[PDB]
Amino acid sequence: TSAAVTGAAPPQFDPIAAEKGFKPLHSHGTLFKIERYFAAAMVPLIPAAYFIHGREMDLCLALALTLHVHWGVWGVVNDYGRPFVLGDTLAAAVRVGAYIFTACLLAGLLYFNEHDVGLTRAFEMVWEL
Amino acid sequence: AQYKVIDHAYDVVIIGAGGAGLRAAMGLGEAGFKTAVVTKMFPTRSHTTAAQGGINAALGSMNPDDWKWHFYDTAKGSDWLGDQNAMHYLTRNAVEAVTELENFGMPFSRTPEGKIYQRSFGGQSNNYGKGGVAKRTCCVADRTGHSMLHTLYGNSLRCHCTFFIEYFALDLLMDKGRCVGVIALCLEDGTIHRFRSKRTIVATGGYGRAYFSCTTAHMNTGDGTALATRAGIALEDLEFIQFHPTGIYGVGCLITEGSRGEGGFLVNSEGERFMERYAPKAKDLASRDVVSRAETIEIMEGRGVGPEKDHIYLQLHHLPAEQLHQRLPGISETAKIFAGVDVTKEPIPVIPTVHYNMGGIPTNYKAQVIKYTKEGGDKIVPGLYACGECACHSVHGANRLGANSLLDAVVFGRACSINIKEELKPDEKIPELPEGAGEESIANLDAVRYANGDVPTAELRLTMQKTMQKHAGVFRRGDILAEGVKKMMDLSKELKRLKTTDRSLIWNSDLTESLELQNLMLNATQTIVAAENRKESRGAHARDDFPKREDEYDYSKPIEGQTKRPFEKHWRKHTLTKQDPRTGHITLDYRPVIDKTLDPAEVDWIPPIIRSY
Amino acid sequence: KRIKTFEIYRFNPEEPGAKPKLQKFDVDLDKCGTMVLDALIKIKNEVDPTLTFRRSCREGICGSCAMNIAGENTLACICNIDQNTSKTTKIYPLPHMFVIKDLVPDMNLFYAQYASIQPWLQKKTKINLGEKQQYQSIKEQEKLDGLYECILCACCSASCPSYWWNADKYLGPAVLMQAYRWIIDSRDDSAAERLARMQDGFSAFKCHTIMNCTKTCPKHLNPARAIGEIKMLLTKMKTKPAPLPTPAN
Amino acid sequence: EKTPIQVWGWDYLMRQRALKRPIAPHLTIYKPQMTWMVSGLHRVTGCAMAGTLLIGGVGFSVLPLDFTTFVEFIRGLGIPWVILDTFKFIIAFPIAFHTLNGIRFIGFDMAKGTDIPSIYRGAYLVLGLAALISLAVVVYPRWERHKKATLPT
Ligand SMILES: *Cc1cc2c(cc1C)nc1c(=O)[nH]c(=O)nc-1n2C[C@H](O)[C@H](O)[C@H](O)COP(=O)(O)OP(=O)(O)OC[C@H]1O[C@@H](n2cnc3c(N)ncnc32)[C@H](O)[C@@H]1O
Ligand code: HEM
Ligand SMILES: CCC/C(C)=C/CC1=C(C)C(=O)C(N)=C(OC)C1=O
Ligand code: SF4
Ligand code: F3S
Ligand code: FES
């Protein structure tokens, strides 16, 4: 029989209509720029840390590495910690996890520079054996 | 089994998402109708996207040109089977239509002055035939159907048409001769959708797959013509299958006529430019009906090229490296993939291929589907329109013009929306559906779906493709043809012994392809019998046993002092094939070729002449 | 006589809790066309009509027959069969898509993302439709070569791990390449609000430069170059403006 | 804040989840290529270092057993200089590579060197170059600790 229901328009994106009250301009452009200049700024520093050692490099290795790794694990986390597969709230936790990671990174480095041998001497001593 | 039915209501529905279809969709959309587009595939996958050489319009971007010469060249190529009003409409509105496309985004190749580039093509000329070789063919290099289609598909997203993608059209909805919608299958989930509308537009494209070898998509099964036949409409001129001169020999991919109108030519196994012989004037730029027979003779008579001496060579290698790459990049690559050929160094193996269907659902200049009686003129079919290749307004007579089909789609699509906007008053409410609405359409599906016979869909189709090819070939003869009509009509019997396997509803390839074999047969039978009963030779139709063109007068002599042969004795007439789907029985009838132009004041009707290129 | 075996990914949504399986078919290489699609149409015609896949043009221009053949996303129709028969070849659908049945992906997300970019032509001063062609110089138009050619086949997207993890938020190579086709088309007046539609942290910036999109593209198009060109505009470099229609045009 | 498409897209996912459709095989089946494995590597190196810099710093705070006493809780475990210098390599290489490749990937971001030949020259040049510099930094200072153990003077 042809005695059955009325159906609706199939799910379909209408790029004008949905465009209406959804005009926002909050650009990640200017951030992505810097974190590449920052990575490019780090270029000369890595080989410098092979040559010039001691207690002051140790501090800006820690410094600049913390901040790079911060913008870094944040992108790796958006990727593998998506809410589709973790549920909405366990996923927000992984976002917040990110900060905790960036922040324990520094604490831990700072500490190691301040109480143990420092990054650069650490390198030396493993390379001595 | 049992089926779930979904009713929708729209002002206008379009079956087809190709060139034509999408232009109707967007035109009606922009002029504010609630438009549903039904299509068995994603619009971009439609056959229009395969198109190559480009689109004719008298922009005269390359040299001065008058739109009237194009009308001239059109009326000629149609071997006066074309309706001079339709060819009037087509060629006037071409300049606008193509300019629109430029405006819509379509990125045509460019002249130094920065207007649309144009190449020369198969069978066109300046000055009502006298002048030169025309340069009217506008193009996105090599890949114009593609780029055109995309531009249209993108543009149709700006006009809120509601897209029913991968839904297979089963039948038109008929209420006592009026068209009230379509019934389609929705592949993604099994559901059956009746669409109610004020207007339907059948814009479903050709039926190449009827032949064992063609340039067309796997997706050209003439489902629309099947839908017409099936709703009691007779189809016209089915016998005029365009054979394109140059399909790659093995597979039958198409090497565009552009490659010719850019410089390239045909060669036989004697290394002779034999097209100088068959067409002294036009040479390799003769009309495809001619150029093709020309190739097919050279074969028949031992000048065939290759291992078996059975194709010819298209040669472009003489042309500059740069021009080949900027003017024909997409064939360079497909010549290489399919026929191992580097087109700067060797020739492409080519052989005529079934290519285009001038035939289709009859329609007046307005693109409104029509039934026709001898006594009471031609009756409009209310609610129904048809356009693009599935239609027959016959802008093409007996032989299509190169680069006029992308036009005939674009233009008459546009002519659908324009003609509906005009006459669809916002009072006439969406038709209701009648009781039983499209029941025997789901009843077919069901029996085809559970079809238990002992001939698999795959086999029936093959022998219909393989037979249609031997009997309704390039050159035809009555004793092979009538032989053919016999085999064919045994095949419409074998449909009762049809076996399928995939018994499911959610995406059934086996099932849709069987629906398509059903549709193909109706297309093929009608084709072959009309082909058989036409005792003449006009356009693409070539009887070896009635080699002459049979008109009312003999246009070889001076005319002054001759009697008009009566309608029934000459052949200058459209061929209407009525079929009963149930039984497969065809009866013929004939319809007069409209000679009047649209404005006897705007442009002068072109009386028949002898067709020499 | 040489026998090629295929392994085709299989799934029946109609069967109660069925799982994707892997099916093996043997195909006599000397009774089959040269391309994969040909094996594919052979094994459905002769062995198993239930084998399901999309196909149209058969010359690799429509996009329909896209799929994963021997590890790569490519078009079946123009993918040569591995002539060597000691090797067993596997056909799988486009990576990371929801499957409808067998080799047929649900294609819609990608189509809508396509819709999102508004892939049509806009201008600031509304034009009297069919009245004159816009001026575009030849040099200006060739900016589109490598860009209009796209067939929307989806191999690039379906090969890009960013889009595997984020097809909902990241727009993916196919769509961006296209967005770019419209922000460098010298006749379009929207570079500005086009770039504005994809300014956030995901839709464009989630390209982690992996490279699959370009290496795979069956048409030898390079969407990455485009994505990278898009990043530049979203930050530093600028969209050249139109050389004016020189009077006569 | 999701764009209108980002929203549509989530509902799309939720739809497609509701319909129980499987997701088509990806990293299991996709063919290992120089494109995604070097990117893959760039991820891993990058993370592994960061991961060390955590368990390193934090672990040597939160624990007694400090670095000096540990640098020879392992020297006292007589292990051959190749095994030892191979470990240094494995320490050194991530750094070489991730840096080198990092400059590569920024180029990509500027649309630079994005064609299949340029993709693949770099994939190799950056890769090999990094494994040279990591061999230079590890064999050379084991050169002088033999050039001076049995020195000419
Ligand atoms: C075959 C061909 C034709 C061609 C060409 C190259 C090739 C290989 N190059 C051309 C050229 O350079 N210049 C030119 O003028 N013409 C050229 N042609 C001819 C021409 O391009 C085409 O044949 C014509 O343009 C076709 O367009 P049309 O709109 O008329 O039809 P379509 O594009 O084939 O699309 C058909 C649509 O209908 C839908 N459909 C079909 N059946 C159904 C059912 N059962 N249910 C629902 N929908 C259906 C299809 O899905 C499709 O969208
Ligand atoms: C020394 C110079 C360096 C440069 C020029 C550099 C460059 C880059 C670049 C361009 C990215 C973006 C990756 C992407 O989105 O695909 C990146 C990512 C990353 N970097 Fe570095 N980097 C450097 C050093 C380091 C070091 C020493 C570490 C170790 C702590 C590190 C940790 C990371 C991490 C964890 C990512 C995550 C992004 C991903 O893999 O997708 N970087 N780096
Ligand atoms: C959970 C699986 C981890 C893995 C190596 C995934 C593949 C992957 C690879 C291989 C990458 O290179 C890359 N840049 C990603 O992020 C966008 C990826 O997700
Ligand atoms: S960029 Fe290439 S792979 Fe992607 S859709 Fe376009 S043609 Fe297909
Ligand atoms: S693979 Fe994806 S990461 Fe970018 S380079 Fe291509 S879109
Ligand atoms: S069928 Fe058109 S691309 Fe394969």
Image: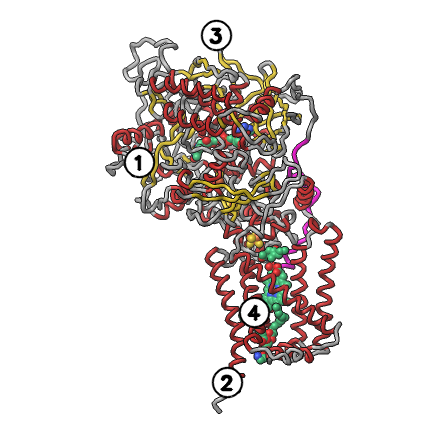
Residue at 31 percent of width and 31 percent of height:
B295
Above-or-below relation of B379 to D133: above
Q: Position of residue A38 (x, y in %)?
A: 62, 66
Is the residue marked by circle 3 packed among few (<14), some (14-19), or many (20+) residues within 10 Å? Answer: few
Q: Which residues are magenta?
A: A8-36
Q: Which residue is mark 2?
A: D147
Chain letter behind tag 4: D
Q: Quadrant of residue B468?
A: top left
Q: Position of residue B244 (x, y in %)?
A: 38, 31
Mark 3–mark 2 CB contact (< 8 Å)? no
Q: Is residue A16 magenta?
A: yes
Q: Quadrant of residue C14?
A: top right
Q: Which residue is mark 3?
A: B375
Residue at 49 percent of width and 44 percent of height:
C6
Which of the two marks, 4 or 1, is nearer to us in this view?
Answer: 4
Q: Which mark is residue D93?
A: 4
